[PDB]
Length: 282
Ligand SMILES: NC(=O)c1sc(Nc2ccccc2)nc1N
Figure (cartoon, rainbow, N blue to C red):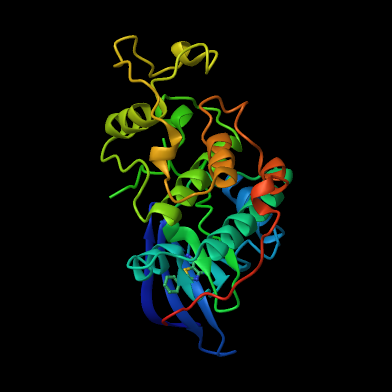
């Protein structure tokens, strides 16, 4: 832009690049995303009215010189960096719980307003010194379509469903929750099929019993290997049983059986939730 002083590049994405920038005028520091249609307008314009404490605020939408810029409030750090920074000791469980609870609130809000994120990953969960965490980079997916991280992709997406639901965000958040707890990505695939098979190897190859309709999925192959489900206590060993029961509900194969963000918020795991302060190195 011209009204902004690009301080530094802070993020990448399929939909563009984000820069820490200063409003040459107001002097405010923001996150400026240069986007890489009309339905895009509605879609975006909607995002502007999608305000909640756990959703990164979209401050301005600039459509000039036939280019698209999104000005977001600047958050202090991303969860990916925080997790890496906390890898020797791990993020304290109360903070993990606080983050999960807040993200579920943000998703419950998005989903009640019929907005899907579609691409949740540690890099787009942003945190501040006050202990808040917020959803960012919705990625205005469902538009510019027709390397990329597949680790958090729901199975129905991998199997070719073209009309997936809010359940895909619960899945992604479940994966992130596991990773915060174990300090290792749950399903670190490096290809769509390896992603899919890593999920199958851990949760068991889905069948009509646990996922009615799965064998009719676009990319489902009868030739898929048949793996047994692994005992969950081996999946996320440091998580207590409440945490594990919530996680299993977030990772149900059937999108229709997968817990909703609203229902997840009432789960016993959050009975003792608090809002700790993270130790951030900025
Ligand atoms: N993508 C976004 O909307 C972002 S990224 C961000 N800050 C940040 C600061 C340090 C490290 C990584 C990200 N703030 C927003 N709004």
